[PDB]
Length: 173
Image (tube, rainbow, N blue to C red; front, side, top):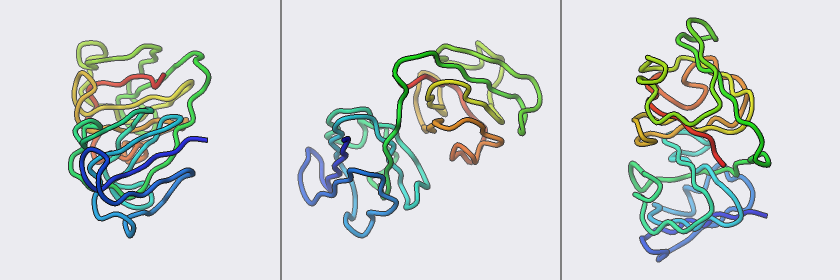
């Protein structure tokens, strides 16, 4: 019973498209997205069809301009609802090299700068043992966003990234 509404202009103006289930392609219904209203739960929204391109994670709320979801442009074309467990334990394993190789670290806590904490600038694979997490390109949860809502990620492309650069990560609660 969650819903997301996309508006072409800022401040919830202009033509609109709404999604109540997952939508793999609404680029023919909206030329651009400059504000969003999210109801009922948390959504992942994507620049290109079929959940491709830049992605952004939006909790319930009102977003009058794309900066409010750290958007890179006003282009969105697909979206899916994020299923969050009832606030249990959260646990993630990050790896120095692809395919779960190299050095590994396991944590239960948000990390606003992984260099100071794990002495890595990059994460080349990961296993999400419990919970749902977000990787960020820059420290303090800034820059590009990548949703980790599955279990195993063998290489960065599996979380939608072109490179293993990750500098912070946190749980979705």
